[PDB]
Image (tube, coloured by chain):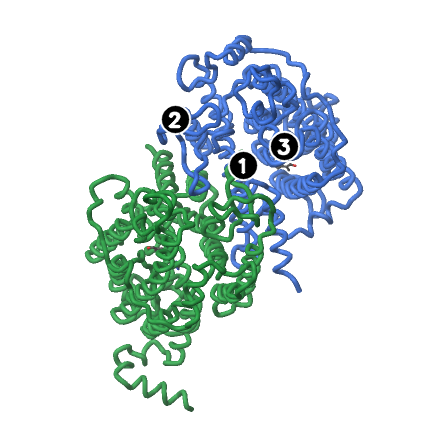
Chain colours: A green, B blue
């Protein structure tokens, strides 16, 4: 009877009256269990998002390169790599981005818990970060838009979404969109994300260049340090097989319904790779590896934001090729939010005939916690679909988001253990999230050619052309041209 | 009453008794209408397959190159292009391949009509030719296997299939395969075929190379003649827009259910491109264009096979990297035939409780008419899924295949009109067939992760790695590893 008296003294306290613990039958233990389940399922993003945004040309630029035998280092030599100053800068930025993402997940999860009494969790999810980490800012200073404007457009989009959802218009704005294009985009983004975690610059290394044909299987061991082409060997890379083993371990966690799956595989691969000396190690004997090991000697640390702190440059909104990014970010956010939260509501005992009793505040918290992320060094956030563990277990009030935020407190003190995760351990998680996103393709009306052609074009043009915007543009254009009357 | 007496004098003739026109209620007019419908739907392959196999490094080799200022032309300079002798050789081979494909479609359609009394049509379909035109023989002499062995493996596979289906084993052989892998392969082959008709060497030219990322949108006009890289311009290619217009015309033929769709778009684009003088023309003012126009001056011709006549080299079955191609061709044929014909049977009034009354001969005719194709210059054939027009209209006997063969007689006399079809008019047909193949993805069990992971891996690894065999191997390996007990 030890649990019963704790539950009832909590319920009769002011917390219980504030959250109405008596109504919507549930106890403190069930809510805590739901919160820990959701955290275990969704904890994979503290490192995945940080690693995605770290190799995305952050504040570090050509001005922070080291000194070489030449007079001054020009552009395309430092951003490529093989330079100590830029590597140290990127290591510091990757160290900072973990704390930035944890703070961005806490601010917004606490808001969703307090302002609205709903059991959800918020953090900067896939999509928008996968969009403006390789398509807008490019890979290490590529593309046309610098990193400063990439946060400015996120701030503008968040403010625009807040304005649009405050006074009621977004309900009538996201309903006129065709039904097939929404699902086609949702599938194409997942396919593109899965494709990203395969190349031999951000993933395991299963795909590379070729002269005659564009893409060829090159999981190859002799790997040129400067660029990444191989001088022999095929499907004998010591790291690719370990990554595949980790992916198999993760995949054999989805069946039999284990609590959290991706995090276990990530930590298994990382723990195996932490061994100093083997050919699969993450700390080599170079001075960079020595510094990384010296920092890893201590397991807990209190890092302070010093590099990518709030710093927004509003001096680039005078040209083209930037407003299109804003338009497509608005489109993607509107596509996601309009469906994910309403679908998530049905699992719980919340959906009513024509209202939700908390929709208005939940939609404003989701958009509201985007300015805080833009002036932090991260991208837009969204209600997580992979929070169904809590709704399946229990808990109908704001003891899920608050406890998730309290757990995320105990996630930024372990920065040394989250900064040395190898790049090849991320790939399996990206592939798994691509599979989960693609799982919805069975809801598309493939019968009539009008929807089938549009869906196929939108799905295909995203991974091949390596740009999310082209798929949406080509889907909308085909749908408009076919329906000309 | 003019039609009635023709119908009854045909029925009471020996043809009617031989085909049992009285039973399986139907008349001569209905069967002829069904045959013309099937021919109009499926006539798109006389030129598509010829164009696919023409730029696949045919008998033409380094020994047929012209004379230049150097002593002798080495390998990688002639097969690339920009040489008169090789261009003339490839033009002659493309001229011959149309007649070869027409003969291969006739022999086998007549057999399916006479030996078995079923209304189907046979021709070398997509898949196997898309496989051994860019993956085995490669693009113009690439890869590891010469063109001579590519026909030898087809002959061996056809003989093996005939032996396997003669004495009953293939019924119990194609049933132990997992259900998800079959559909995953069927979708991946379609995706790969659609991807093929996009590159700027065999398709419209929407996809090309890039340094940082592997694939980038490059529908670009300034196009280097030697290789195909552009020195400026984007999405302003005068031929890409015409190809897109043709694709739209074809797509606005699938709704409203017009008889044949792809052929109309192909002939529209080709007729527009036949104009001499414009920047989109197919006959330029170079001597090659002058010779092509001189041959096009006459509209009808009786071409005789002179280059790729039966010529099989059985001297390469001593090494590796060839038996794997045989195994995967056997796998693909077994995957296709086991489902397409049984599904096609249900539409007609033929399927019974446990038999088909004609399955045994139909399965042997399909495999039997592969040796004749191998010793002709083409690839394996299969019963066409896009013959549903006849079964929907009428006709329950062998007046469909015989009339289809008679029509294919009136398709090789028009070689000049089938040899000058531009390369950019083929792409829309490839994309449309990719859409039709992908349409089946809704039948895959995406619920459980065991099937979803396998299906996603098999679907994704085909277009990215640019090889059909890798997708099948990676699907089978994952399915075997996940189910280890
Ligand atoms: C809505 C956006 C991205 C969509 N991503 C996600 N949307 C919903 N749940 C998730 N879990 C992980 N990532 C996501 C960006 O605004
Ligand atoms: C079975 C094979 C290829 C599958 N291709 C096709 N299978 C069935 N119908 C068709 N129509 C056009 N192409 C096809 C090769 O043996």
Q: Residue at x 53, y 36 (%)?
A: A213
Q: Earlier in the sequence, mark 2 or mark 1?
A: 1
x then y, percent, for residue A17: 26, 81
Q: Which mark is residue B150?
A: none
Please, is residue A161 above or below residue A470 in the view? below
Q: Could you tell me which chain the residue with mark 2 belongs to?
A: B
Q: Could you tell me which chain the residue with mark 3 belongs to?
A: B
Asked if residue B40 lies left or right of residue B236, the reply is: right
In the rendered image, which quarter is residue A336 located in?
bottom left
Label 3 element class: loop
Label 2–label 1 contact, CB within 8 A: no
Name the residue beneath numbered marker 3. Answer: B137
Quadrant into which the N terminus of chain A falls: bottom left
User: Distance from label 1 to label 3 (Cα)?
Assistant: 16 Å
Determine if marks 1 and 3 fall on one subunit: yes
Name the residue beneath numbered marker 2. Answer: B221
Q: Residue at x 62, y 39 (%)?
A: B344
Q: Nearer the viewer, mark 1 or mark 3?
A: 3
Label 1 element class: helix
- State yes or no: Cβ of the residue under disc 1 lies below 8 Å from any atom of ligand 2: no
Quadrant of ligand 1 in image: bottom left
Please, is residue B463 above or below residue B95 in the view? below
């Amino acid at each position: 009877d030890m649990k019963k008296h704790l539950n009832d003294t909590v319920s009769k306290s002011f917390i219980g009256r504030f959250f109405k613990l008596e109504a919507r039958k549930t106890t403190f233990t069930t809510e805590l269990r739901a919160a820990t389940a959701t955290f275990l399922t969704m904890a994979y993003i503290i490192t995945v998002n940080a690693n995605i945004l770290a190799d995305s040309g952050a504040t570090c630029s050509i001005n922070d390169c080291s000194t070489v035998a030449s007079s001054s280092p020009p552009g395309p030599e430092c951003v490529l790599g093989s330079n100590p100053g830029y590597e140290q800068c990127i290591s510091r930025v990757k160290k900072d981005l973990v704390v930035a993402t944890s703070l961005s997940a806490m601010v917004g999860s606490l808001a969703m818990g307090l302002l609205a009494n709903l059991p959800f969790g918020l953090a900067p999810g896939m999509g928008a970060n996968a969009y403006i980490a390789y398509n807008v800012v490019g890979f290490r200073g590529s593309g046309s838009i610098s990193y400063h404007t990439a946060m400015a457009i996120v701030l503008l989009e968040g403010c625009a979404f807040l304005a649009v959802s405050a006074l009621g218009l977004r309900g009538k704005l996201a309903r006129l969109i065709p039904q097939t294009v929404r699902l086609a985009c949702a599938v194409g983004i997942g396919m593109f994300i899965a494709f990203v975690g395969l190349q031999m610059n951000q993933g395991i290394g299963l795909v590379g260049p070729d002269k005659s044909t564009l893409v060829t299987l090159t999981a190859c061991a002799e790997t040129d340090p400067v660029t990444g082409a191989c001088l022999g060997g095929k499907m004998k890379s010591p790291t690719f097989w370990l990554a595949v083993v980790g992916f198999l371990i993760t995949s054999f966690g989805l069946m039999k319904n284990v609590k959290g799956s991706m995090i276990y595989g990530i930590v298994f691969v990382t723990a195996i790779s932490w061994i100093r000396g083997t050919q699969v190690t993450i700390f080599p004997h170079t001075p960079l590896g020595d510094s990384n090991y010296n920092y890893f000697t201590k397991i807990v640390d209190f890092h302070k934001i010093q590099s990518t702190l709030g710093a927004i440059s509003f001096t680039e909104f005078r040209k083209s090729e930037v407003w299109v990014a804003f338009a497509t970010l608005f489109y993607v956010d509107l596509l996601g939010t309009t469906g994910v939260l309403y679908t998530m509501a049905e699992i719980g005992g919340f959906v009513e005939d024509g209202k939700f009793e908390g929709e208005y505040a939940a939609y404003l918290v989701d958009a509201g916690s985007s300015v805080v992320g833009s002036a932090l060094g991260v991208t837009t956030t969204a209600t997580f679909v992979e929070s169904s563990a809590g709704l399946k277990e229990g808990g109908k009030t704001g003891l899920t988001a608050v406890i998730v935020g309290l757990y995320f407190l105990a996630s930024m003190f372990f920065t040394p253990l989250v900064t040395n995760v190898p790049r090849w351990a991320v790939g399996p998680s990206l592939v798994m999230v691509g599979v989960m996103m693609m799982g919805v393709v069975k809801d598309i009306r493939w019968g009539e050619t009008k929807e089938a052609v549009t869906a196929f074009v939108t799905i295909l043009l995203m991974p091949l052309t390596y740009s999310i915007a082209n798929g949406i543009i080509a889907g909308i254009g085909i749908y408009l041209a076919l329906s000309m009357y």
